[PDB]
């Protein structure tokens, strides 16, 4: 049936029979200066939808940078020196029964991406545009400081078909339309500066191209909604 | 033992029937301005205003008694032989229709309380409950109704208690008759909060707390004098 | 406070967490972590600086924070004095203090053996 | 002795033998859309000190406007439509034993102040400068939209000597140096728009002029520190 989920002043709609992929089998928790929690940040931040077309390569978001300007939790990234949060990423897909296509929705921890120019580093804008998705290309990328965003190598110098090693979900339009991934906090330190470290990125790569019957809508909206979980920060006490 | 403080109480102090307004309305006129009206206010009579403004918030019922007396005027009309005069005192609750003419549609008073009184009987009486979406009338308001407008300082719509309207139901005679209403005001079931100093400087405007600065008391000749 | 016993006054002993930046006005110091050190009430003020870092240990060499003091009020005295007061500062470690990797101090230096 | 009080990341110093005047005998509480509390606002906001001189009339602050730009609780006044808070006002005074003077520290609920021009209303700037104190004058004030800030009438058309009817404290420098007044929320409505309604003002009127021995400091600092208590707001839920 229909499941209604409310966090804070945000409500989303989910199917009862929705499969949830929980990271590496780990549910986000706190680290049980005393760290300060912020439950007000536990909201649904629905990003702008991306139009999935017949010739559309994948997208990616880097979420510390993606939610950097999303009201609360963005003010908290700007405010607190140290921060920690797990995320519930819910990727919806609005399509009819006459639409085709398969999607790989994968969250990649520490997706250090290469540059189009070998003797160069990608700049901040190319790696993450924030709430705006960065798109892959079907061919090699050219640029002095641009990310090598060819789809086959997923920007990481690996095989895109091997991306399933990370917490992923398959959206087959004839079978599924949604993907819920619950990513815990993954890092080599208990807590890190959020403004300069993307702990993971979300890649939505269409492995089977979108197709549709004549007269059906050409594009299929893909909606990403992110709910930070167990977010806690530095804490300012004693003088 | 201890002496009784009964009449010093806020109920006895404030629940005293006083005249707060009087107006005269004609029986015939050129326009329809043959009616008296009074926006119910507590800031027009200095004694009552001072007594109420000794507190910050008050909550009371309005008991109103109307003393209506009619006088025949001048001359030039003979065989007057007027029948008995009937008066209508219409109360308009806050947000209710407000007449502009003696024969306005508002006088048909679909929901405005109205009392019809024939002369010669006991004076008409009506009681207005505590009417405010707030929890108490505020004699003082350190704020703005709209923060943008400077002239809205100290005004809040929570103290509006309605308007009283008076007129003649029948003219009686074709000659001039003028009636005075003489409204008598009496709070009932008074609860007051946050007592305040009595107003020292004389009042200037009903809708203001503005004042010409005045000395704290009367002077004397010497700090050691006795008379 | 090393002033007179009759001297009175207040200070803002404000602490800035690392990365925040030193306050530039009295108001910014007050809006953060601070104490009102009243000279008349007490001549000493002990301020325990917490441990705020992303790792268990940090390098001794070159954020850490800031201590700033602000004139909340001027120093008030029986209005006859000439010279000014002084404040002495002390530093100490708390019971949770530790050091990991021993090395050579950067302070003593020798060209060769002293004999 | 010495009592140290810590609220949030603020610490102040108080004497053990400090008398506290609790409003009208009422300790601030909550009203027990569901109202939302904010304990982060429960901090000590130390205003800029005011110099008490030999010829200094009183000052006043209107506290919804005074704390309007004090970081938190100021952001909350700007953010929430409805708000409620009690206040702990602590007025300190730094003086030696060679200084004279007496102060009336009084918090006046609903201090609707008159204007210098009778057919006029005081403007927002004259009534409250915010964190900056507004000063009384020893003579009549002149201005089209200025508050009648003569000391004798306390700006309210009453006797300044009768101001003790409100929750007050006397600071006799030979006896006291501090004043703590705990003011609950006083209003005719359960909760009001804070940006346009000063629920009470603090008046610090020197009834006995400051005096000092030769060589002693001419001015005496007066420090006002305000701690909001039991602050709660509108709440944004349901859609």
Image (cartoon, coloured by chain):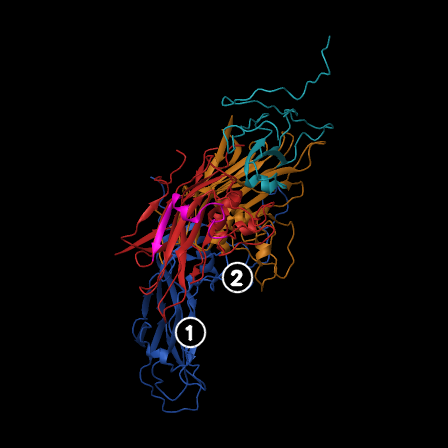
Chain colours: A red, B blue, C cyan, D orange
Where C109 falls versus A99 (above or below)? above
Residue B195 among those drawn in magenta: no
Residue A151 among those drawn in magenta: yes
The outermost residue toward the left is: A1
Q: Write the residue at 54% across / 50% down.
A: A147
Q: Secondary structure at mark 1?
A: strand
- Count of numbered labels shown in the rendering: 2
Return the disc, 2 or 1, that comes first in the chain's sequence.
1
Viewer-side residue, A187 vs D140: A187
The percent coordinates of residue B182 (x first, y second) are 40, 70
Please state if D177 lies on the left or on the right of D83 as rendered.
right
The percent coordinates of residue C55 (x first, y second) are 50, 31
Where A218 falls versus D90 (above or below)? below
Q: CA distance from mark 2 to mark 1?
A: 22 Å
Q: Write the residue at 30% across / 71% down.
A: B122
Viewer-side residue, C7 vs D32: D32
> In the image, which disc is placed on residue C62?
none
Please state if A24 lies on the left or on the right of C86 as rendered.
left
Please state if C108 lies on the left or on the right of C49 as rendered.
right
The percent coordinates of residue D147 (x first, y second) are 59, 56
Which residue is the site of mark 1? Answer: B37
Circles 2 and 1: CB distance less than 8 Å? no
Which residue is the site of mark 2? Answer: B208
Residue range (magenta): A150-172
Residue B107 placement: quadrant = bottom left
Residue A86 placement: quadrant = top left
């Amino acid at each position: 049936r229909v499941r209604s989920i409310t966090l804070g002043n945000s409500t989303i709609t989910t199917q009862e029979c929705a499969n949830v992929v929980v990271g590496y089998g780990v549910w986000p928790t706190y680290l049980n200066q005393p760290t300060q929690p912020d439950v007000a940040t536990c909201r649904f931040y629905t990003l702008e939808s991306v139009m999935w077309q017949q010739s559309s390569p994948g997208w990616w978001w880097k979420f510390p940078d993606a939610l950097s300007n999303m009201g609360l939790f963005g003010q908290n990234m700007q405010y607190h020196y140290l921060g920690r949060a797990g995320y519930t990423v819910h990727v919806q897909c609005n399509a009819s029964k006459f639409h085709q296509g398969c999607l790989l929705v994968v969250c990649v921890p520490e997706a250090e991406m290469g540059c189009a120019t070998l003797a160069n580093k990608p700049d901040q804008k190319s790696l993450s545009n924030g709430e705006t998705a960065n798109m892959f290309e079907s061919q090699n990328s050219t640029g002095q400081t641009a990310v090598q965003a060819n789809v086959i190598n997923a920007g990481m110098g690996v095989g895109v078909g091997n991306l399933t090693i990370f917490p992923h979900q398959w959206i087959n339009l004839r079978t599924n339309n949604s993907a819920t991934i619950v990513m815990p906090y993954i890092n080599s330190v208990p807590m890190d500066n959020m403004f300069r470290h993307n702990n993971f990125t979300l890649m939505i790569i269409p492995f089977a191209p979108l197709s549709y019957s004549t007269g059906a809508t050409t594009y299929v909206p893909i909606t990403v909604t992110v709910a930070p979980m167990c977010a806690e920060y530095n804490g300012l006490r004693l003088a | 033992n201890y002496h009784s403080r009964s009449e010093s109480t806020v109920e006895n102090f404030l629940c005293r029937s006083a005249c707060v307004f009087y107006t005269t309305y004609r029986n015939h006129g050129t326009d329809g301005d043959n009616f008296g009206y009074w926006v119910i206010n507590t800031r027009q009579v200095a004694q009552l205003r001072r007594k109420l403004e000794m507190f910050t918030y008050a909550r009371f019922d309005l008991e109103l008694t109307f003393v209506i007396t009619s006088t025949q005027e001048q001359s030039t009309i003979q065989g007057q032989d007027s029948p008995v005069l009937t008066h209508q005192i219409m109360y308009v609750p806050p947000g209710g229709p407000v007449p502009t003419k003696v024969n306005s549609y508002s006088w048909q008073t679909s929901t405005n309380p109205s009392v019809f009184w024939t002369e010669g009987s006991a004076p008409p009486r009506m009681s207005i409950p505590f009417i405010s979406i707030g929890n108490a009338y505020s004699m003082f308001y350190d704020g703005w109704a709209k923060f943008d407008k400077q002239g809205t300082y100290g005004i809040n719509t929570l103290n509006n208690m309605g308007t009283l309207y008076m007129r003649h139901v029948n003219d009686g005679s074709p000659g001039p008759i003028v009636s005075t209403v003489r409204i008598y005001f009496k709070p009932k079931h008074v609860k007051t909060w946050v007592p305040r100093p009595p107003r020292l400087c004389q009042y200037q405007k009903a809708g203001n707390v503005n004042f010409e600065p005045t000395g704290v008391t009367e002077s004397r000749t010497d700090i050691t004098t006795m008379q | 406070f090393c002033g007179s016993a009759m001297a009175t006054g207040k200070f803002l002993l404000a602490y800035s967490p690392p990365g925040a930046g030193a306050p530039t006005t009295r108001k910014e110091a007050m809006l953060g972590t601070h104490v009102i050190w009243d000279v008349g009430l007490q001549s000493s003020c002990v301020l325990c600086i917490p441990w705020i870092s992303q790792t268990h240990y940090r390098y001794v060499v070159v954020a850490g924070g800031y201590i700033t003091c602000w004139y909340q009020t001027n120093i008030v005295v029986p209005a006859d004095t000439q010279s000014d007061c002084k404040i002495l500062c002390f530093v100490s470690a708390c019971n949770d203090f530790s050091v990991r990797m021993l090395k050579d101090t950067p302070f003593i230096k020798q060209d060769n053996f002293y004999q």
